[PDB]
Length: 24
Image 1 (spheres, rainbow, N blue to C red):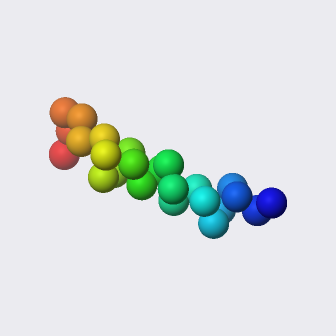
Image 2 (image 1 turned 30 degrees about the vertical axis):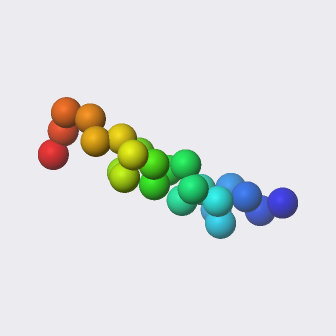
């Protein structure tokens, strides 16, 4: 299935909302 675009925001978002590492 096309879970590479409609699902990319699934794990990716976690890097912007779940991964608040030391960076601005």
